[PDB]
Structure formats: structure tokens, C-alpha cells
Image (cartoon, rainbow, N blue to C red):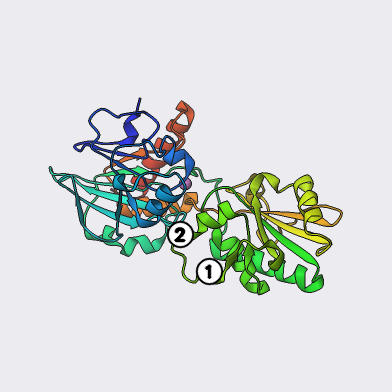
Amino acid sequence: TCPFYKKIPGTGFTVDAFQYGVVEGCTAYFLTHFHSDHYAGLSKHFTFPVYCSEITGNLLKNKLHVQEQYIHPLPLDTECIVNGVKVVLLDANHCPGAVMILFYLPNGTVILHTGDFRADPSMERSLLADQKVHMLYLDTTYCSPEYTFPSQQEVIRFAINTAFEAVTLNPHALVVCGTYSIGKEKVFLAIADVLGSKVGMSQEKYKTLQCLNIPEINSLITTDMCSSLVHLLPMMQINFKGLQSHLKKCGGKYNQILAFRPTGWTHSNKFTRIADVIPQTKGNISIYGIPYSEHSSYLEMKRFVQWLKPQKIIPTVNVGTWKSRSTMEKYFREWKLEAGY
Ligand code: NI
């Protein structure tokens, strides 16, 4: 049965609630973005209206085969009426197509559901600045102060310079980047760009990237592995076994692999700086884990909430334990007392 934090009171709306069968009273199912924990339950046999971004809609049609008549894409930054309720989709600074949703309730309550997001000061000059928000359904993934990580810009700088250096030393080195869902495309596109190559990948992954409205994408990616010196592989294949087996398949074109594993946060973040990160190495294979996050750090989350000053906060992540729930409520109270709302 659908949990309360996926229901929008005063509406027939749910968010990211596709795995509970038919939700009693729900006239429209919103999908924030195309990640499996969020879309879980959707398939080509789903027969209720889905509201989402254009990019999320392209992926529902082409990857899950949801029929077109049930896909309702909405433009961003635009006031739209859905079943008699005004809504706005805003960019969530998560993966492609990911949105936050503002719901303007008939009784005058305003609700922001962040979906999955990485809070940014630029959101303080979106349509959010224009009115008050009473309830906030918040992505609390990293809501604890030990969760620090660098900016996306710094991480990409590290990766570009690492890759460029390795391949200029050895023109016979192959770069491999791990992937399992959309998001974090910047990692492999920046590296390929600095090396003057397209990114090579499977037909299934190429299809996925073709849904994302990335400008000039046809110039950046290919299914011809032979012509490319940046390859994508499934994340599970980024280990010494998987990589050796992949190097065998390239037919003596390369004698070295440098591989990147974009992770979320990892405990090495409490000690080590990004400058200082080193790979794991076995023979002619090196593997960097890099902390490229598409979720708020603690400090980014704190800033956004203190700026927004919501009257009530409802967490959407880490809700399954009493210890987590209790930890989160403590930080919300701190933030509220520090800022005076
Ligand atoms: Ni996500």
C-alpha cells in the first residue's frame, strides 16, 4: 500500500508511486525522473495517465514501452492545469529529465516535492522565489554532516586531467567508464571531448542516450566500438576481471586500461581530498572511484531549506528506520532555530 509521503493531500495525485497497483483515489501519477527506484512498477501494461518531463516521456515510450496515450509530458518553468490544479515542473539538477514539482492547492496551500535533486543556489532564482511554500517533500539522501563531496566541476576537472595525462603518455591506453542508469553523462562526455573521440557503447545504451535531448549528441556517441577510445560498460563489469576480459575483445588495439567508477558518496570523503585520490591497480589496469554526486551534499541541502523556510518538511529518503527519522528531525529543528523561521 502506498505510503503517505508519496501522496499529495487535497488532490488525486501521487508522486513516484507505480509499484502499489491501483492507488485508491489517484487520478494522475507523477514521475519525477527515470530511475528504477522511482519508476518501479511501470511497464507497457500501465493504463493510467502519467505526468512527467519530455525526456522522462521519451524514455517511458522507448525503453519501458508505455503506450503513448498515457504519457503526458509537460514543459518546465510553465504554469499548467492538471485535473483542475495548477502545477509547475522545475529542473531538479539530478539526471536528465529530472524535475521538482510545485503544486498550488485549491485551498491556497503551496507544496514543493523535490523528487531527487542536487540543491543549488540557482534554484533561489527560479519560480520558487515568487511565493511561499508551506510543505516540502525533500530528498534527504545525504542529510547528515559527514556527507561532504566536491562540486561536479572539480570532479570533472580531475577526470579530464587524469585521462588526458594517461593517454598522452600512452596512446595505446583505453579509457572505460562504468554506467547503470541515466545521470552522470558529463563524466564520459568530458573525457571523450578532451581525447578527441566519440564515446562507444552498446546498442541498448546508445538508445537510452538518444532519448535525452542532448545537443549535438550524434557528434558525441557511437555504437562502433572500434573507432572509439572511450568505451562505456555496465558498472558491474568495472573490476579487474571484467576489464581484462574487455581488453581481450579489443584485438591488440590497446595494452592498458584506465577506468572510472562514478559512485555516490564514499567514507574516503571524510579524509581524502579529490586532488589526492589514487586508483586501484593490477598490472596494466587502473580503476578510479570518483565522487560525482547528483544529490545534495548536507551543506547544499541545509542552505536550500534555510532559504525556502518551509512550514513543514516531509522526508522521502531514509524513512525506514526510527534512528534515521529521528536524526533528520533534529537537523530540521537546528536549521529552523538557526535561521529564525
Ligand atoms: Ni534518482
Q: Residue furthest top?
A: 1
Q: Which residue is mark 2?
A: 212
- The residue drawn where x is 50% and y is 51% is 297
Kindly tell me whether mark 2's CB lies below 8 Å from ligand 1. no
Total marks in image: 2
153 sits to left or right of 224: left
**Foreground residue, 305 or 84?**
84
Residue type of the residue flagged with mark 2:
Leu
- The residue drawn where x is 45% and y is 44% is 64
Answer above or below: position of 214 versus 282: below
54 sits to left or right of 147: left
- Cα–Cα gap, marks 1 and 2: 12 Å
Say the numbered circle drawn on residue 97: none
Near mark 1 (Cα within 10 A), the count class, few <14, some 14-19 or many ≥20, is few
Q: Residue furthest left?
A: 107
Answer above or below: position of 39 versus 201: above
Say the numbered circle drawn on residue 218: 1
Q: Quadrant of residue 111?
A: top left
x then y, percent, for residue 271: 67, 51
Residue type of the residue flagged with mark 1:
Asn
Look at the numbered disc 1 and give the secondary structure of its residue.
helix
x then y, percent, for residue 270: 63, 48
Answer above or below: position of 14 versus 164: above
Q: Earlier in the sequence, mark 1 or mark 2?
A: 2
Residue 183 in sight from this viewpoint: no
Look at the numbered disc 2 and give the secondary structure of its residue.
loop
- The residue drawn where x is 79% and y is 55% is 247
Q: Quadrant of residue 54?
A: bottom left
**Foreground residue, 133 or 115?**
115
